[PDB]
Image (tube, coloured by chain):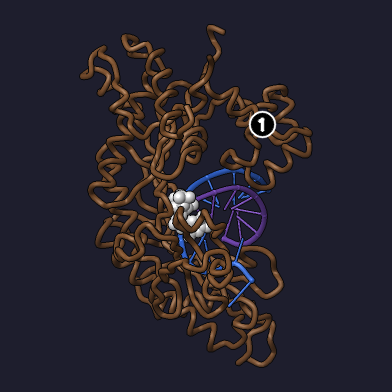
Chain colours: A brown, B blue, C purple
DNA sequence: ATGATGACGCT
DNA sequence: AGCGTCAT
């Protein structure tokens, strides 16, 4: 009890842009706003692959990874925006630039870790301290939390969705201990006021809406984010964890959505995150390894220590294209041509990066998939990246992969390539 | 024929 | 180094 750490030491948020590529296209084209719409890449095979979906289209069953032609059977009035195509591949520059717009705004409030093109974690611990002093010991108005849900409330002795939100919020704030500058629940609340302000700023300055989770660590912040979407934010307190976890499938917790999560379920014969509390740390470590067992033991109690890394910029800059089915690359000249295309996009991105962010990449990773392999990558090789020159980079990547060709006739490439990937890495200051 | 990315762990 | 996992 008096020596048990409760993982209540930080305030962490996760901010996630709602249907982000869709919002980028809707800002640009007002005819798409407030409509069922999706973002598609390519167009020939089955209308293109959907990669993002507006909340109005999701109500019809439209999802990512559906073909647009199939999405149209569920939602006949679905509007589509197409990803730009440059040098015969998808080019995500518009979405990268929009993400930078958002991240720069977030960075005014606190330390951010870029988690993906449209998510960042935020460490609010310091911001909350500072804000607790100036606000003094005076109370926090619900009007400062207009889009916040307090997970697990209301509870105890209304018919509308906004009404439930306000009821829980009132219960929370009515129990808050406002004169104890170290109360975790108070710290979270202030964190949430800050996140409201951050979200208001993003929307005002970009037009983009997002959801957010506020809790004591990244895993709980991420989970919290997804609980009330879109355009809302959710506070998951330490106290809320036992009930929340008691029915929370294991696969919903970040890092457990794959093979390890499935093994936890199979080996232990459990279904929900809270059920982990029944095992000793050594038991868990015995099944899953020292690092994973320790992490699971703390996580199922709501405790997690992964720091929010101060990193707003990606650490690698890469370009790839899949060549599925009949388009698989089968001649030396095709392979070379496509490496050049990839290397030209890459050069463009790298030069821009070098001007914007004062750094230079030094390693080039070359990855390919071959026809028949159900892995992301059949093969990865590195080479020095000494000049930002597309012809050099493509020539080098070719060199590095060329003996993968089993074909006897030199013009041909067997087995055919179903993926090419160039990745610039090992950045240094410039 | 679920694409184009990106981070990190294991050995 | 190069492969495997998990994620958006
Ligand atoms: C998961 C995922 C996302 N994305 C892009 C499209 C989304 O617009 C953007 C953000 O991903 P997300 O946060 O997973 N999804 P979303 O932002 O579209 O939707 P949500 O509102 O966050 O659910 O990333 C992909 O291109 N491929 C993916 O597999
Ligand atoms: Mg999102
Ligand atoms: Mg996201």
Q: Quadrant of residue A74?
A: bottom right
Name the residue at 63% across, 31% down.
A296
Quick one: which residue is furthest to the top in this view? A2
- Element at label 1: helix
Q: Is residue A36 toward the left or the right of residue A27 in the image?
A: right
Name the residue at 48% across, 58% down.
A57
**Is residue A425 visible to us here?**
yes
For disc 1, does the CB lie below 8 Å from ligand 3?
Answer: no
Q: Looking at the picture, how far across and down is residue A238, in whole percent?
A: 50, 22
Residue labelled with disc 1: A293
Quadrant containing the N terminus of chain A is top right
- Of residues A404 and A76, which is closer to you in this image? A76
**Is residue A360 visible to us here?**
no
Quick one: which residue is furthest to the left in this view? A134
Q: Looking at the picture, how far across and down is residue A83, in whole percent?
A: 41, 70
Q: Quadrant of residue A198?
A: top left
Q: Looking at the picture, how far across and down is residue A123, in whole percent?
A: 37, 33
Q: Is residue A403 toward the left or the right of residue A349 in the image?
A: right
Q: Is residue B4 toward the left or the right of residue A192 in the image?
A: right
Instruction: Tell me: residue A414, above or below residue A142.
Output: below
Of all chains, the one bearing label 1 is A
Mark 1 surroundings: few (<14), some (14-19) or many (≥20) residues within 10 A: many
Q: Looking at the picture, how far across and down is residue A252, in whole percent?
A: 60, 40
Name the residue at 25% across, 40% down.
A108
Q: Exactly how many numbered labels are in the figure?
A: 1
Q: Is residue A153 toward the left or the right of residue A263 in the image?
A: left
- Of residues A322 and B9, which is closer to you in this image? A322
- Of residues A255 and A343, which is closer to you in this image? A255
């Amino acid at each position: 009890g008096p020596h048990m750490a409760t993982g209540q030491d930080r305030v962490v948020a996760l901010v996630d842009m709602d249907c982000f590529f869709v919002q980028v296209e809707q800002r640009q084209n007002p005819h798409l706003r407030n409509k069922p719409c999706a973002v598609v890449q390519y167009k020939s095979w089955k209308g293109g692959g959907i990669i993002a979906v507006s909340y109005e289209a999701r109500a019809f069953g439209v999802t990512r990874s559906m073909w647009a032609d199939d999405a149209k059977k569920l939602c006949p009035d679905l509007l589509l925006a197409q990803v730009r195509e440059s040098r015969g591949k998808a080019n995500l520059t518009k979405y990268r630039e929009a993400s930078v717009e958002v991240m720069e705004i977030m960075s005014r409030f606190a330390v951010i870790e870029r988690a993906s093109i449209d998510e960042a974690y935020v460490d609010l611990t310091s911001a909350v301290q500072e804000r607790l002093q100036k606000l003094q010991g005076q109370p926090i108005s619900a009007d400062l939390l207009p889009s916040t849900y307090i997970e697990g409330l209301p509870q105890g002795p209304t018919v509308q969705k906004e009404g439930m939100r306000k009821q829980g919020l009132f219960q929370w704030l009515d129990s808050l201990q406002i004169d104890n500058l170290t109360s975790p629940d108070l710290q979270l609340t202030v964190g949430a006021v800050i996140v409201e302000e951050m979200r208001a700023a993003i929307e005002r300055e970009t037009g983009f809406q997002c959801s957010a989770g506020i809790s004591h660590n990244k895993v709980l912040a991420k989970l919290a984010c997804g609980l009330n979407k879109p355009n809302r934010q959710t506070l998951v307190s330490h106290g809320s964890v036992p009930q929340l976890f008691s029915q929370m499938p294991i696969r919903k917790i970040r890092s457990l959505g794959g093979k390890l999560g499935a093994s936890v379920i199979e080996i232990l014969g459990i279904e929900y995150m809270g059920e982990l509390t029944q095992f000793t740390e050594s038991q868990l470590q015995s099944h899953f390894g020292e690092k994973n067992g320790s992490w699971l033991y703390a996580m199922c109690r709501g405790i997690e220590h992964d720091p929010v890394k101060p990193r707003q910029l990606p650490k690698t800059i890469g370009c790839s294209k899949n060549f599925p089915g009949k388009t698989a690359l089968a001649t030396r000249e095709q392979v070379q041509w496509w490496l050049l295309q990839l290397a030209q996009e890459l050069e463009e991105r790298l030069t821009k990066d070098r001007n914007d962010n004062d750094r230079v990449a030094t390693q080039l990773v070359v990855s390919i998939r071959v026809q028949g392999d159900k892995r992301l990558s059949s093969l990865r090789r590195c080479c020095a990246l000494t000049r930002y020159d597309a012809h050099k980079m493509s020539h080098d990547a070719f060199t590095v992969i060329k003996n993968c060709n089993t074909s006897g006739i030199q013009t041909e490439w067997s087995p055919p390539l179903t993926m090419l990937f160039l990745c610039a890495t090992k950045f240094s200051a410039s």
